[PDB]
Structures are given as structure tokens and as C-alpha cells.
Length: 129
Ligand SMILES: [Cl-]
Ligand SMILES: [Cl-]
Ligand SMILES: [Cl-]
Ligand SMILES: [Cl-]
Ligand SMILES: [Cl-]
Ligand SMILES: [Cl-]
Ligand code: NA
Ligand code: NA
Ligand SMILES: [Ru+3]
Image (cartoon, rainbow, N blue to C red; front, side, top):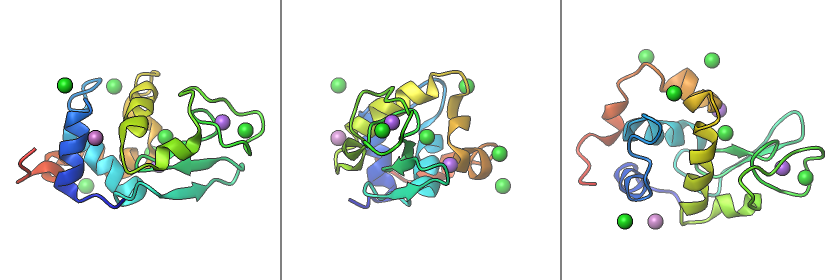
């Protein structure tokens, strides 16, 4: 599923990301924009052999099991395929664990490079929610 901007904002709010760990809704929408272009089916292989999955590009090195990332962990206790669903529940629940690990949203390189420090409220401007 490719979400619209306001559609994803509303879904993320419903799923409890608004101000989760102190990160306003626009931070999460901005991260999803640049990680996946709002496409739940996005996948990208990393040089080390791990793969990033879903709207928030969650990495099989640590967070999910894909059966092909030797020596990795599965800290969200989910198959990586669950992160590709049209329903964002699995991605949101795993993202909540990631953002709570100590480094906040800096875990998402696209967030650090393209959202951090910017007017992220623009990502939710005009949305009904
Ligand atoms: Cl509720
Ligand atoms: Cl990630
Ligand atoms: Cl594996
Ligand atoms: Cl933080
Ligand atoms: Cl950086
Ligand atoms: Cl800027
Ligand atoms: Na893994
Ligand atoms: Na990134
Ligand atoms: Ru939902």
C-alpha cells in the first residue's frame, strides 16, 4: 500500500506514534516519506547482507527475522514480512521499540539527514487526523 501523507499521519496517530518518546507526528511522517516514500512494500538490501523492510525500513540485522541475515537478532520478535503489510501495526510496534533503545530517531538515517532540525510540522499541515 502507498499511503497518502495525511492518511499515514492519521494512521500513525491512531497507532500511538504522536509524541511517542517525545517525537511529534511530523517526525514520523517525515521519516516514512524519506525511508519508503510511504510504500508499505518497500525493501532495500544493505551491503552487509541485511535488508530493510516496510514504511520505516526496519533492519533485519537487529529487529526482525528474514532467515537470510546470519548472526542477526530479531528484537521485535516478528518475521520481516510482517513489516510489509497494508496495516501498519507491526511496523509501528517495532518502531516503538527501536526509538526507545537509547538513540531515539537517530536510528533512522534518513530521519537524521533529512528530517531532524527541520520544520517537520509541515508534514501534517492541513490534515484532518
Ligand atoms: Cl484506542
Ligand atoms: Cl531502522
Ligand atoms: Cl537470519
Ligand atoms: Cl530522544
Ligand atoms: Cl547523519
Ligand atoms: Cl533544511
Ligand atoms: Na534478523
Ligand atoms: Na535511513
Ligand atoms: Ru490501522
